[PDB]
Amino acid sequence: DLYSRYKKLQQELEFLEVQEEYIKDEQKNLKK
Amino acid sequence: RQYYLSKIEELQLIVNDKSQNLRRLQAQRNELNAKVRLLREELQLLQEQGSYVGEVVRAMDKKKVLVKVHPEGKFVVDVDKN
């Protein structure tokens, strides 16, 4: 319960950070 | 108990703002994509040649028109489906 929620929250943070980096790279590519 | 709750709350708020930022960034990306695509279609539609301009003498068929292209002359042309 608590540990599962905490672990999924870390996973979803890491996933969202990956999406942020990917979107920033796509923004630079689209500007080019 | 309280360790898990505190960690979960910190992660909840941080990932909530992360998700809002991600939605904003994706909206901006889609706007840039729209701009780039519009420019690309403008280029493509500019590469096609200009079409001739001619007056219609009369319609001959349900699919053929007797036009007069200046200065080439008169043509029996076919009609587009639109």
Image: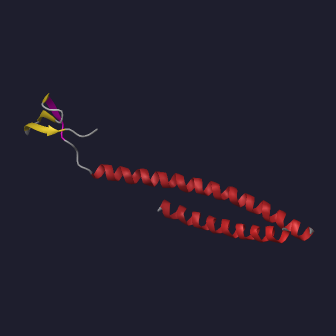
| x, y percent for residue B37 | 43, 53
Which part of the image, by quadrant, shows the N terminus of chain B? bottom right
Drawn side of residue B7 relative to residue A17, left or right: right
Question: In the figure, residue B55 lies in which quadrant?
Answer: top left
| x, y percent for residue A13 | 72, 67
User: Which residue is at a point 48% across and 51% down the rendered structure image?
Assistant: B34
Say above or below: B43 vs B5: above
Residue farthest toward the right in the current orientation of the protein: B2
Q: Magenta residues: mostly which secondary structure?
A: strand
- Return the residue nearer the eye: A20 or B76: B76
Question: In the figure, residue B29 lies in which quadrant?
Answer: bottom right
Residue farthest toward the left in the current orientation of the protein: B73
Q: Count the labels in the image.
A: 0
User: Which residue is at a point 79% across and 62% down the rendered structure image?
Assistant: B12
Drawn side of residue A32 relative to residue B42, left or right: right
Drawn side of residue B69 relative to residue B11, left or right: left
Say above or below: B26 vs B67: below
Which part of the image, by quadrant, shows the C terminus of chain B? top left
User: Which residue is at a point 45% across and 55% down the rendered structure image?
Assistant: B36
- Return the residue nearer the eye: B81 or A6: B81
Whether the magenta-drawn stretch holds residue B18 is answered as no
| x, y percent for residue B59 | 15, 29
Q: How is the image coloured?
A: secondary structure
User: Which residue is at a point 84% across and 63% down the rendered structure image?
Assistant: B9
Drawn side of residue B11 relative to residue B68, left or right: right
Q: Which residues are magenta?
A: B52-56
